[PDB]
Image (tube, coloured by chain):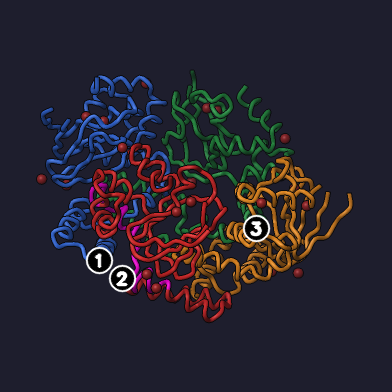
Chain colours: A red, B blue, C green, D orange
C-alpha cells in the first residue's frame, strides 16, 4: 500500500536525478505526487478489473458522490446517465499556473471541476470552480479551443475524452442540450 | 497460488479503506472475491497465452463441460461451434439484487447461465436459470435492452460481447436462427 | 532464467489442480512446456522491445537461420523479404494428434514448418515436413480452409497471420506468386 | 534503479546464451545496452503515466532541450508546435554500420538527429549530423524510401511515426512546408 508509493517515488527520484532535472522542478514533481496520490498507491485499473459491472459502478458512484452533488449537470438527471458519465471519467490533478487547455489547439477532452479554481482566457479573464465544467465547445463543434485555461489553484479535475463524450451522448442523446446551452 | 489471492485482496482492503467505503459495502466486496475467486488467484490470460490453440481449446471445453451440458443451444450442435463460442466467453459472477442488464440502455453483450437465477423484468417478472441465456435481442436487432435483468441469487454467468457474437455467427451463420427463435 | 520457468509452471500446476483437470491431461500440458520452453523462460517481447530495429532483425535472422535454409520459399529471395517475413512470424509448438487447421473453418493464419510432420486431409491424406508451408490458400482466396491438418509428430512451426501476410505482400507484391503456384 | 538494469541485462545474457548467439554478437548487444541505457533503467512510460499533461510536457521539453537547440526546424517555431513534436518522438540509439533505412522499402517513420553521423546513399554518398532530419520524403509522398541510411557513428536519434507525423501536421498544417522544402 504505502510501500508501493514510496518505492514508485524512489524510482521517480532516480529518474529525475538521472536526467539532471533542476531542484525546483524536482520539488514541483514531489508536490504533485503528494497531492495526487496522498502517500498511497494502488493499481486501480487492476483492482477494478477483478470486480464486476455492478461493483465497479457502485464504487465510482460512491467515490464521486461529492462531485455529483456539486454538479448541476446531474441536477435532476437520470441515475444511469450519471453512471455512464462517471465510469468514463479520468481523475487528474493540476498545479497552480498549469495550462490545462491552450487556445487554438485541437481539443480531445473536456473537464469537470471537483475542487479548485481555473481561469478561462480568450478578451478578459473568467473564473470557474467546483461543479462547473469546461472545454466542451470544441467537443460539440469539433473546432479549435475557444480559450486557454490556466490552473489558478490546485485543481482536482475529472476529464472526459471526445470519444467517451460522444459514446455517452449516443446512449443519452437529449443530454446533449445541457452541454450546448452552457456553450451557446 | 493462494498467496497471490491474499496479497491481491489486502490491496483491495487498503483501496476500500483509502476511499472510506462503508462497512456493509466492504462486506459485499469481500463476499464477491470469495465467490468469484475461491481463495485462489491465477493470471489465466497469462497462463493460457503460454499454451497453443489446441491446449487452450481443450481446457475451455473441459472447464465448461458442465455449462455445455446444461445448454440446449449446444443440444446437437457442431463441436467446433461449441468451441468457437466457449473460447470467446468471459466468466462473471453476480450477486443477489445486482442489475445485470438495464432496460432502455445500449446492449453490448449477452449472458449464458451456468448456475443461478435471474429475473427478467419489462409487464410481469420472469425467471431464467441454468442452461438458458438472455440479452440476445439487442444483439440481433441492435436496438435497446428490451428488459432489465436483476440477479435473484448468486449467478455464475458467461458473457459474450456483440463483436464476438457476430464473429462467431460469421463462421456459423445458420446457428443464428437458434438465437432468433428464442427472441422471436 | 530457469527460476522463471519453474515458478511459471508451478502456477500452471496449481491452475490445473484448481480446475481438477485429469491426470493424463496434466501430463500432456507438462510435456508441452518442456518441448516448447525447454526449462528456461524469457519475456522475449520485453527483451526485444529494449533493442532497436537492426538488433531485433539480426536476432530473428540468426534464430531462424536453420528454418530459412530449409525453405525454398527463400530459395533465392531478397534478404529484406526474408527479414520482413521472419520478424512477423510467431513460434508455436504442436503435439501429435493436434488439429492445427480444421476444414471448413475461417482461416486467419498460415504455417511454416521448421521441424516435424503434418497430415493434410481433405480425399486421401498427404504429408508435409521441414521447409514446406500450409494454410496459405484461404489467405489468398479468403475462402474457408480447404483441408484439415492434424499434427503427426511434435511440430515446431512458425505461424503468420493474414494481416501480416498481406502487409508483407504489400511491400513485396511479386512474392505473392510463390504462394499462388504452391496453391494453384 | 541500477539494480533493474543489471537484472534486465542478466536476462538478456541468458537469452543470448540460450539461443547460442556468437561471441562478437553478444558483445555488440552488450555495447548497445551501455550506450542506450547507461547502466540505469526506468519504466518511463509507467512513470510518465503517473504524471499529468503539463508535467510530462515540461519533462520532454527539458530532456530534449539540447536537441531542440540544434534543430533549425524549431528555428523560430511555435513553442506548442515544438511540444506537439517532442511528446510524440521515440528515442533510439544506433550503432556504426547499422541500416536505419533501406532504399525501396515502405517507410513508416522519419528520424531527427540528436548526436551522430549518418550516410545517405541513393548516386554518391552524403553525410548528415546533429540538428538535421531524414526519411521525411516517403512520409510526405507516401512512396518508397528514396535512399538507404547506414549509421556511420553511434547515433542518438529520435524517430517519428507516419501517423504521429500526420497528426502533428493536422494541428500545425503550415509547418508542413518546412519538411517539404528540405525534400523538394
Ligand atoms: Br469553457
Ligand atoms: Br473548447
Ligand atoms: Br492552491
Ligand atoms: Br490538490
Ligand atoms: Br436522453
Ligand atoms: Br431476454
Ligand atoms: Br436485450
Ligand atoms: Br443465493
Ligand atoms: Br457464486
Ligand atoms: Br452454420
Ligand atoms: Br495446404
Ligand atoms: Br487453407
Ligand atoms: Br514425435
Ligand atoms: Br517439439
Ligand atoms: Br516484389
Ligand atoms: Br533524406
Ligand atoms: Br524517405
Ligand atoms: Br562512434
Ligand atoms: Br551512443
Ligand atoms: Br500551422
Q: Quadrant of residue C171?
A: top right
Residue B17 visible somewhere in the drawing:
yes
Q: Nearer the viewer, residue A62 or C39?
A: A62
Main SS, magenta residues: helix
Chain containing the residue with disc 1? B
Residue C30 visible somewhere in the drawing:
no
Chain containing the residue with disc 3? C
The local secondary structure at tag 1 comes to helix
The answer for how far apart the CA atoms under marks 2 and 1 are is 9 Å
Q: Quadrant of residue C138?
A: top right
Chain containing the residue with disc 2? A
Disc 2 Cβ-to-ligand 4 distance below 8 Å:
no
Disc 1 Cβ-to-ligand 9 distance below 8 Å:
no
Image quadrant in which the C terminus of chain C is located: top right
D47, above or below C90, in the image: below
The answer for how far apart the CA atoms under marks 1 and 3 are is 42 Å
Q: Nearer the viewer, residue C163 or C180?
A: C163
Q: Horizontal and vertical percent for residue C76?
A: 74, 38
Is A111 one of the magenta-colored residues?
no
Q: Which residue is mark 2?
A: A1
Q: Which residue is mark 1?
A: B10
> In the image, which residues are magenta?
A32-55
A39 with respect to A96 (left or right): left
Q: Residue at x 53, y 75 (%)?
A: A16
B128 with respect to A15 (left or right): left
Contact? badges 2 and 1 (CB < 8 Å): yes
Q: Residues within 10 Å of mark 1 (few under 14, many from 20)?
A: few
Q: Nearer the viewer, residue A29 or C45?
A: A29
Establish whether labels 3 and 2 are both on one chain: no
B91, above or below D76, in the image: above
> Any mark on residue C55, and which?
3
The local secondary structure at tag 2 comes to loop
Amino acid at each position: 500500500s504505502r510501500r508501493q508509493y514510496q518505492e514508485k517515488y524512489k524510482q521517480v527520484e532516480q529518474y529525475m536525478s538521472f536526467h539532471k532535472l533542476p531542484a525546483d522542478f524536482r520539488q514541483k514533481i514531489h508536490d504533485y505526487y503528494e497531492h495526487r496520490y496522498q502517500g498511497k498507491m494502488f493499481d486501480e485499473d487492476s483492482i477494478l478489473g477483478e470486480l464486476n459491472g455492478p461493483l465497479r459502478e457502485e464504487i465510482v458512484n460512491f467515490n464521486c458522490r461529492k462531485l455529483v452533488a456539486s454538479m448541476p449537470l446531474f441536477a435532476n438527471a437520470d441515475p444511469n446517465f450519471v453512471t455512464a458519465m462517471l465510469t468514463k471519467l479520468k481523475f487528474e490533478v493540476f498545479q497552480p499556473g498549469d495550462y490545462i487547455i491552450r487556445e487554438g489547439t485541437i481539443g480531445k477532452k473536456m473537464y469537470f471541476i471537483q475542487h479548485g479554481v481555473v481561469s478561462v482566457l480568450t478578451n478578459k479573464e473568467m473564473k470557474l470552480s467546483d461543479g462547473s465544467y469546461f472545454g466542451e465547445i470544441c467537443l460539440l463543434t469539433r473546432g479549435r479551443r475557444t480559450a486557454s485555461v490556466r490552473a489558478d489553484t490546485y485543481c482536482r479535475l475529472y476529464s472526459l475524452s471526445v470519444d467517451n463524450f460522444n459514446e455517452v451522448l449516443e446512449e443519452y442523446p437529449m443530454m446533449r442540450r445541457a452541454f450546448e446551452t452552457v456553450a451557446i
